Length: 73
Image (cartoon, rainbow, N blue to C red; front, side, top):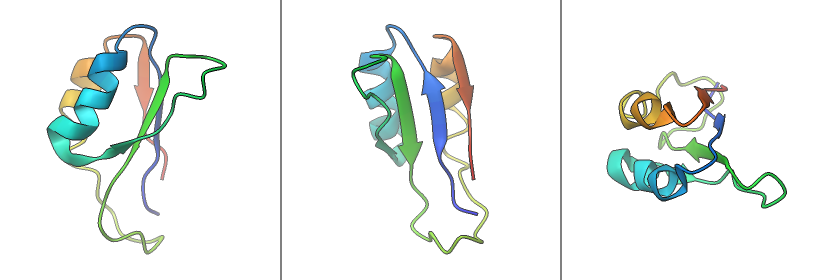
């Protein structure tokens, strides 16, 4: 119970990395093989039992317009 938002985005690259910086998360989702995927991870309390991921519910979906965006705890 932490948070791992995985999403595939074709061109929102500059935005993907921008979200993490805009809200406050570490974006790591581009493997290069798919060159579009981008995932954020930030909570400051990864105790596998701490609900959070609130600030990531703004520029995430807003930027998610690219294609699709979903979280994963």
